[PDB]
Image (cartoon, coloured by chain):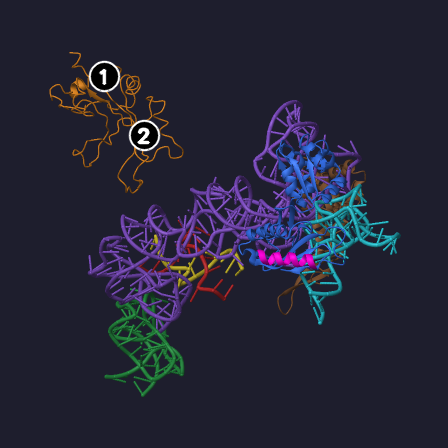
Chain colours: A orange, B brown, C blue, D purple, E green, F yellow, G red, H cyan
RNA sequence: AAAAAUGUGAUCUUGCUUGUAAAUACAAUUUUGAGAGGUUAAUAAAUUACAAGUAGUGCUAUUUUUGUAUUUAGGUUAGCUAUUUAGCUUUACGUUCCAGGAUGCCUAGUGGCAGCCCCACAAUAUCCAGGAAGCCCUCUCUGCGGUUUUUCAGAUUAGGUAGUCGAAAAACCUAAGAAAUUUACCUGCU
RNA sequence: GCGCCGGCCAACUCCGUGCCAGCAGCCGCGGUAAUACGGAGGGCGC
RNA sequence: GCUGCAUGGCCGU
RNA sequence: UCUGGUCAGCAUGGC
RNA sequence: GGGAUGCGUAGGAUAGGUGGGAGCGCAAGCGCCGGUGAAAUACCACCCUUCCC
């Protein structure tokens, strides 16, 4: 029972692409004093016409979560811009964060996404034992039974703090 | 030239014609009043800082400022040589007065609500008691230029 | 150069010295050598002390700077003694110090005293080449005094030649030659060319004429 | 910095030559837009520090007390024109912007002012002119720049001089086939 | 009946026309108000 | 709506 | 004199 | 080789140097001494610079 219940594992915020803290190391400042940690990431994909053609990229991305830091964040997080907080918005797996997608090559990849819900929010929902699949060892796979359902997912969060819409 | 020399009414305080001329040089936009004031106030400035009577200080200044010789260009067969020549007595005054006011305006010191200190300081600096200041420089420079091309 | 040749030099020199059979006073033997193909400008010049194997015959004037014991020995020897107390006084009065330096060929000083002597004395003594030789406070001076007497200084200066006192009329020709050899040894060591540098060598008594080797 | 004392073997120091070490920065506006390529090819100035040799000078070579301190400073060796003062900018000769560092040199003083701690003025000459930008141009994306082919009758009613490349078209820029086709000053005959 | 009617050269208006069609001995005329082209009415000459 | 080269008038020079 | 400017002030031939 | 020659300052003075040196001389003088100086000088020598033969 309690096992079946859905809770949020790692969320992680993120930022847009391009260089960050261009004038001075900034934009990391936001994400700072927000969420508590300070991630930074880099990128690949050299020739960008209006992007850089830098290889190793300063590119801003970051955040993550845990338990309880993203609760008390993802608190006063959701209840931010959500014209349609949920619906079609997230999908089979449980949760999402998106907006309007573009015709781009997708699907055959690990599936990180451009998608921007908020400063592209990533609530990811998983119930269960699930640490099973992720963890290195006999990985195991999710049952596709005890898997999240969007319906269940658009529950839990909604029951608390904010309407589904 | 421009016209016949018109005689100028002498100064109300000290009935010196030369003074009025100086005042005219200062004035612009026909603000005759401000112009007279600046000169008068300067004279008062000349009195305090310097024991001497202002009228004397001014006249001496003009004397130091008047160029005796100036160079005028002329076209010779080749190139335009700058012929040195004397300067009319009338011409010398206009140059002297004009140069004083210009140099006076030149001074950094912005004293009195107006220009009045710059005039006061300029004149003293001019005197040859103190023969220095921007006004005298121009005067000395012209004379130097002349007789260079004697 | 060779021993036999010098022996002849010495022997001849003694015979030549005359006027009478011999002066009343004992003359001394001088050895003079001229050098060639050496530039005096460089540190080619020689200033050095040589201990002669058989003494000079005069036993060079020597001064001793030091305190009791060392000073006592000096007095017994009959040498001038400069006491520890005097050193500062002498530094102050250049007039006396200059005189003292001119009068004596060598100076021996208690080793501990060396800091003080150069501080005060060094300006006068050093230029001269007069700087004292240190000896332990409780050393036995006699052997040294004998050698320094029985020591002679070879000082070329900028000039090409050298004159040194080798001995006395009293000493044997063999001894004079031995002493000359010690002098020659220094030159041999100084330049790579060695003795080759010696242009000419001569021996002579005080009164007597010089004879070329 | 001043004072006193011990004292390293008294003692004492302005320099010349060789070896090693580090700064002197850089970015930006602007440029044919951007990146990459020799910001080249060249040759690297000079300031301080330690060692040795050497005239120097015997070489490394001390401790205690006192005021913030009572010290020297400041400038000076940028280019250009000029017969002097001066002036201009502020330093350029591969071209653009800028620092003056060595030695030696100058004022320690003169003039105005009631007075000054208040304003003005001197200084030779040799050393390197050094540092960054910057390089005919080339390749790529591919460039408000600018290519590729064709046609050219005829000015409210027509001509005389003529209008940025003579005009126009379509289109090319990884590709250039392909087709239509003006006017301003100014005027007329029976 | 025949030629001519812009000037030389005597005899003029309308319409058609539109650098066309045409005229022309010379100067020239016609590119939309042409006594100059073509017809018509009128006129001059013979 | 065209033609100030078909013009009046008026104006500039 | 400039085929100066204005038919867009008005007037006016022609289109 | 013989005769000349050697000018910072201080030093009675134009100190090229170095070794010997407490004397050389009837004396005068000269030196030591004293002193100045980085160095001391008579007298005996040797080594030099420049000039002459």
The quadrant of the rendering that contains the N terminus of chain A is top left
Q: Position of residue B22 (x, y in %)?
A: 73, 46
Residue plotted at (30% across, 17% down): A72
Q: Nearer the viewer, residue E43 or C101?
A: C101
Q: Nearer the viewer, residue B149 or C142?
A: C142
> Residue under circle 1?
A158
Q: Residues within 10 Å of mark 1 (few under 14, many from 20)?
A: some
Q: Position of residue D187 (x, y in %)?
A: 40, 68
Magenta-drawn stretch contains C195: no
Q: Position of residue D86 (x, y in %)?
A: 66, 51
SS category of the residue bearing label 1: loop
Residue A42: quadrant of the picture = top left
Q: Position of residue A73 (x, y in %)?
A: 30, 19
Q: To which chain does the residue with label 2 belong?
A: A
Is residue D94 left or right of C152 when viewed as pictured? Answer: left
Q: Residues within 10 Å of mark 2 (few under 14, many from 20)?
A: some
Q: CA distance from mark 1 to mark 2?
A: 31 Å
The disc, 1 or 2, on the residue closer to the chain's N-terminal end is 2
Looking at the image, can residue B30 be seen? no
Is residue B70 left or right of A117 when viewed as pictured? Answer: right
User: Looking at the image, is A90 positioned above or below residue C18?
Assistant: above
Q: Nearer the viewer, residue C90 or D22?
A: C90
User: Looking at the image, is B23 positioned above or below residue E16?
Assistant: above
Q: To which chain does the residue with label 1 belong?
A: A
Looking at the image, can residue C105 be seen? yes
SS category of the residue bearing label 2: loop
- Magenta stretch: give its range: C3-15
Q: Nearer the viewer, residue B112 or C134?
A: C134
The quadrant of the rendering that contains the C terminus of chain A is top left
Residue A148: quadrant of the picture = top left
> Residue under circle 2?
A40
Please report contact status of discs 1 and 2: CB closer than 8 Å, yes or no. no
């Amino acid at each position: 029972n309690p096992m079946r219940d859905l809770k949020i594992e790692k969320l992680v915020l993120n930022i847009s692409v391009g260089e960050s803290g261009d004038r001075l190391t900034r934009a990391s400042k936001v994400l700072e004093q927000l969420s508590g940690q300070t991630p930074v990431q880099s990128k690949a994909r050299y020739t960008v016409r209006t992007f850089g053609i830098r290889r190793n990229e300063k590119i801003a991305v970051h955040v993550t979560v845990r338990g309880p830091k993203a609760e008390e964040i993802l608190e006063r997080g959701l209840k931010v811009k959500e014209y349609q907080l949920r619906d079609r918005n997230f999908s089979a797996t449980g949760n999402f964060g998106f907006g309007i997608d573009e015709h781009i090559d997708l699907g055959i990849k690990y599936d990180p996404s451009i998608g921007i819900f908020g400063m592209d929010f990533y609530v990811v929902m998983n119930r269960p034992g699930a640490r099973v699949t992720r963890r290195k060892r006999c990985k195991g796979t999710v049952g596709n039974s005890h898997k999240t359902t969007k319906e269940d997912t658009v529950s839990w969060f909604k029951q608390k703090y904010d309407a589904d819409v | 030239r421009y016209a016949n020399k018109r005689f100028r009414k002498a100064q109300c305080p000290i009935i010196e014609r030369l003074t009025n001329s100086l005042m005219m040089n200062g004035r612009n936009n026909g603000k005759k009043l401000k112009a007279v004031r600046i000169i008068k106030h300067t004279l008062d400035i000349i009195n305090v800082l310097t024991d001497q009577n202002p009228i004397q200080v001014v006249v001496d200044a003009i004397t130091n400022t008047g160029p005796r010789e100036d160079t005028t260009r002329v076209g010779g067969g080749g190139a335009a040589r700058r012929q040195a020549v004397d300067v009319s007595p009338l011409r010398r005054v206009n140059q002297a007065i004009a140069l004083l006011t210009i140099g006076a305006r030149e001074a950094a010191f912005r004293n009195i609500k107006t220009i009045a200190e710059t005039l006061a300081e300029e004149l003293i600096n001019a005197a040859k008691g103190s023969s220095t200041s921007y006004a005298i420089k121009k005067k000395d420079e012209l004379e130097r230029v002349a007789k260079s091309n004697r | 150069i060779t021993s036999s040749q010098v022996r002849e030099h010495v022997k001849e020199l003694l015979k030549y010295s005359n006027e009478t059979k011999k002066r009343n006073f004992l003359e001394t033997v001088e050895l003079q050598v001229g050098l060639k193909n050496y530039d005096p400008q460089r540190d080619k010049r020689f200033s050095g002390s040589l201990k002669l194997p058989n003494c000079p015959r005069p036993n060079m004037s020597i001064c001793i700077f030091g305190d009791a014991f060392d000073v006592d020995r000096a007095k017994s020897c009959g040498v001038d003694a400069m006491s520890v107390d005097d050193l500062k006084k002498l530094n102050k009065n250049k007039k006396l110090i200059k005189k003292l330096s001119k009068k004596y060929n060598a100076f021996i000083a208690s080793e501990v005293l060396i800091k003080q002597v150069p501080r005060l004395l060094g300006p006068q003594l050093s230029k001269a080449g007069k700087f004292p030789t240190p000896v332990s406070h409780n050393d036995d001076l006699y052997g040294k005094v004998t050698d320094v007497r029985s020591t002679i200084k070879f000082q070329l200066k900028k000039v090409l030649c050298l004159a040194v006192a080798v001995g006395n009329v009293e000493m044997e020709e063999d001894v004079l030659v031995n002493q000359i050899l010690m002098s020659v040894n220094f030159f041999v060591s100084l330049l790579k060319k060695n003795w080759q540098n010696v242009g000419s060598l001569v021996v002579k008594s005080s009164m007597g004429p010089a004879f070329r080797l």
